[PDB]
Amino acid sequence: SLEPPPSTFQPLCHPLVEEVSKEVDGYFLQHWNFPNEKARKKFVAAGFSRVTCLYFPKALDDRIHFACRLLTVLFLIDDLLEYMSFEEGSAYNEKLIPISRGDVLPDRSIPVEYIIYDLWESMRAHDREMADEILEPVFLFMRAQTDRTRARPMGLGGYLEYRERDVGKELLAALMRFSMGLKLSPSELQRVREIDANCSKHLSVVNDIYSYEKELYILCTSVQILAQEADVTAEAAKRVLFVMCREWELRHQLLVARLSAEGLETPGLAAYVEGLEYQMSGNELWSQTTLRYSV
Amino acid sequence: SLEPPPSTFQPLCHPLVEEVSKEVDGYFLQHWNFPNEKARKKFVAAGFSRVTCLYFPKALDDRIHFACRLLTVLFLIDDLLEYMSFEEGSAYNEKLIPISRGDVLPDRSIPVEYIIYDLWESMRAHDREMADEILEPVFLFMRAQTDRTRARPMGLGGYLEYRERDVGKELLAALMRFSMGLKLSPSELQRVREIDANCSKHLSVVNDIYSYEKELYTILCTSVQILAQEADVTAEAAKRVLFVMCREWELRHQLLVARLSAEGLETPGLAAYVEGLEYQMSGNELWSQTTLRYSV
Amino acid sequence: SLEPPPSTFQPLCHPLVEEVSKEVDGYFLQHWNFPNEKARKKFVAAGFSRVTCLYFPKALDDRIHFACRLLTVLFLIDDLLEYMSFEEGSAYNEKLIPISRGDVLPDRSIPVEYIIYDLWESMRAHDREMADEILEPVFLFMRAQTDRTRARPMGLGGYLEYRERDVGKELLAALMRFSMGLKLSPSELQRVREIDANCSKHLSVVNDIYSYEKELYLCTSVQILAQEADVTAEAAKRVLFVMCREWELRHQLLVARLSAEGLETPGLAAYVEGLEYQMSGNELWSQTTLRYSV
Amino acid sequence: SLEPPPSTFQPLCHPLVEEVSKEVDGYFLQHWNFPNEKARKKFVAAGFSRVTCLYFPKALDDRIHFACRLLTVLFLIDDLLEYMSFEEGSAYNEKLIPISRGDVLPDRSIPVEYIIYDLWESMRAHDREMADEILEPVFLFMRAQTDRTRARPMGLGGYLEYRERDVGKELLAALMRFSMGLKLSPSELQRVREIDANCSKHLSVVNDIYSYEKELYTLCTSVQILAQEADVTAEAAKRVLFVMCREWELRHQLLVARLSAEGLETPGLAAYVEGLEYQMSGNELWSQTTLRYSV
Ligand SMILES: [Cl-]
Ligand SMILES: [Cl-]
């Protein structure tokens, strides 16, 4: 057992977790075309809404279900793209994008299509401004799902610089903003780029730490890279990476304290950086428990 | 102020430290032309022999003074080289290599010359063969504190690899054997490859951690800066991560030592060698944290 | 000598180049106040519109001048920045952004301000949708001129990946679409990311090759390769040039594939060809511009 | 399909190749225990002596056969090591080192053992001091033939710095000196360090270029590294690496010119660096024709 090192952060779950969870889970079991009974209860066991509530514990009470719905359908779609070629998976997603914009009408006979359509319709109806702002982050993520990335020599610095721009973590930060009703200005966002990049690496590395065993069923992970650079075992590497993650949590506290001392911390940004902290503690807890990293 | 993480390595100090320290410091205070008392006291206060006894606590009682003398002159030289050009520097040293070999007699007018000559002649008297074995390592080390640094990009991986072969660490390990009267076969040292690389890396990084602030008086070329940049954190955060890495290399050392005895096996010689390296790693750490050589 | 190796890419030049040059040069010679009659004649000598016409040989006739003016001003601001702190520079640029948006009026007392204002007001007047689409790429680029590089080890592979995402090259390819009046949806844009990344690299490396010398006073493919291979800078440029010819062959292959997989469209076919012209034009320009102290 | 770019170097073979080949071949056919008449044909077919004469065309007439015998037995052992574990192979070679020094007698009933003993005994009988000088280079090479590589992310720069210190190339340069009777002082050798390093990369890269297809039969090669750092195909990388090799040929000539311009190029040094030039052109022709790189 790894034994995480001490941390000043702590996981927190959204207050309405049980309530939203049943609501959203019901919706999908009702509308989604699962293959069989095994898949049906594998889905309930996954508890995507509980995942979402762990990542956005501070979302507004009336918007958390939106987040759960979006993440649930993306998790479902993600798992589906596993069984299809590049050309089909890409074609699959590109078709849902115009529908997501509301520009194209569903084929009410195809679950994923009307689920996606209705979802975005309802989000815009609740807040068009913020709903439109999160469209691109989602599309970016959706396009990356069928992305064929190059295997190339990559040291620790290159790998981390690359994770700093991860679109998955970007989608999470934007979805968090929507869930919290935090309309951040262009200026405010620029002010927390370092904080975002720092957070993005944290989430990524913690995922790497707990997914390595499974990854070692194109292996691109910080555990292998550090193990090879330092000439130690994967486990020793996980230990070193975990301490690096704590260094990043301390960096987060410092970047935030600085922001405030310079008087650049607005109420919106305060909620935001705190939201990120819970995304980090949440992701860690999720990583330690998710069945997706089992084997 | 930087709390080193827990370690199973316990450093030792050679019993005769006070004895040799007096003998060897007395010699140099008598022959080396120290500019003044201020330099005399600093030299003593630096106690180069105490450093030697910390790195080689298992050295044989009658050889430890050799190591102290050798290292003391190399530290005194090393000190002078920073007041010269790479060309002067290389000239100053290259002139001392023939003298170390014995082929060229001292100009008893230049202390360093006859101190180098007399010491080497004395080492052969005791054990000619072994005193000959460390000649290369000694020159390789001198033919390096003058060589130019071939720029080129460098990540953590490449920097660590390059340190696994540090010629300073090799001289230390070679000086250790001569000091412990260890005589390993060409095959024996071949069996501890990974152990020597892992140790040289430990020693280098611990040095990096404690010499960073001073080095940052200027380019750098140190694991501290490299990790700080690659992970995007402060140098202090980097020192703490690198320290944890050092403990991993200590755990790796033990595992490599285990496999060595289990798998096939060691030798009385390799068992002594291998333990010796452990003492270097811990002695090096105590030294790095206390030496003024890293003081700003 | 530095003899460029053979290339199947033939640069093109916009036929209206002379017409637009005197048109645009004259414009700045009237409003842009240079230091002396020499800095002036030096300007007309650089001919930034010729550069534009090499890059966008197929820009629409009634739009090529927009491109010329935008680059002519980015190049002028460029040289201007080289003489002020990373504070004075970022301030300067940051006030040209809202004004570029039309949200803030140009203090008519400062030329660069109203030149920018009128240029953008003018582009929106011609095609408001496509004009707003380049604001971002232009801003990203202007912001980039004012920040100091990162601070981490970088080998050839990382430097080349870093260049596949060059701000300037993205600006050029967005200016090009505006110039050719090419309305490309983000979906079609997706299908050519490899081609764009490939092109971006070609442009940056050819630039590194000819600007190395001037940059004598760094972050460049020329120095990185010279250190990695342990050869002279001149030898590195020669190896880099052969690599560029490989990227040109790659472009051709990517283009054939895009066409083979039923993914090609008339607008993409045009965009893809346009990037080719940029590669060959940029090379011709790089070999002759005085900007690099030929 | 792969056309070498123009070069100012040219391959050359040793005048006595036909004579030495017959002799050295005959010796091994007589003493080496080839399994069956089949392996004997394959052996003569390999022409290890002919390869030696391609790398050492300036060898003295009375010493070229020493080089042929040494390389022949090394090529033979190299192949045998293929059917052993790293540990077994290591023990095998470690046995032959004390015999090479002449410190331990051969077991006259084990061919490799007495063939090794007799070769060195005869080399020391021809030129004692120089023969003893090549001992270390041969042992380094013999030991390197069996240790682990250790996979680690590596860019073009790190891979080339590695090849600069290749023990194989160090063996060829030392053996070339013994074959040409060039006694080089410790100072002369240091003046040629850059040149030696430059030459090493050339031989290795040229070997990489032609051995690549063979290596793809499932790793660590300049072809692989460059294709992915530049993001082009292996074939394109080969074309680019070949031009780089030519740049190293120019650099060799330039380094020699400077060495000469300054006052440090003795006659021994001059014959040495010319010797390296033919090793480079020879290795190229060999790389182009050897069956060791085929199917
Ligand atoms: Cl994941
Ligand atoms: Cl030191």
Image (cartoon, coloured by chain):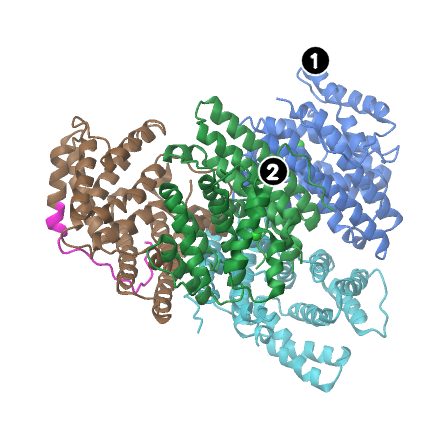
Chain colours: A green, B blue, C brown, D cyan
Q: Which residue is mark 2?
A: A12
Circle nearer the viewer, 2 or 1: 2
Q: Is residue A219 visible?
A: yes
Say which amino acid is labelled 1. Glu
Q: Does the magenta portion include C5?
A: yes
Looking at the image, is D92 positioned above or below residue B249? below
Q: Quadrant of the C terminus of chain B?
A: top right
Task: Find residue D122 and report its horizontal and vertical position in percent.
Answer: 76, 67
Disc 2 from disc 1: Cα separation:
66 Å
Task: Find residue C216 and report its horizontal and vertical position in percent.
Answer: 37, 39
To which chain does the residue with label 1 belong?
A: B
On whether ligand 2 comes within 8 Å of the CB at mark 1, the answer is no
Q: Quadrant of the N terminus of chain B?
A: top right
Q: Quadrant of residue D36?
A: bottom right
Task: Find residue B132 and report its horizontal and vertical position in percent.
Answer: 78, 43
Do dots 2 and 1 share one subunit?
Answer: no
Magenta residues span C1-21
Q: Is residue D263 visible?
A: no
Q: Which residue is mark 1?
A: B37
User: Which of D56 and A9 lies nearest the eye of the viewer?
Assistant: A9
Task: Name which residue lies at 37% across and 57% down.
Answer: A99
Q: Secondary structure at mark 1?
A: helix
Task: Name which residue lies at 68% across and 22% down.
Answer: B292
To which chain does the residue with label 2 belong?
A: A
Q: Secondary structure at mark 2?
A: loop
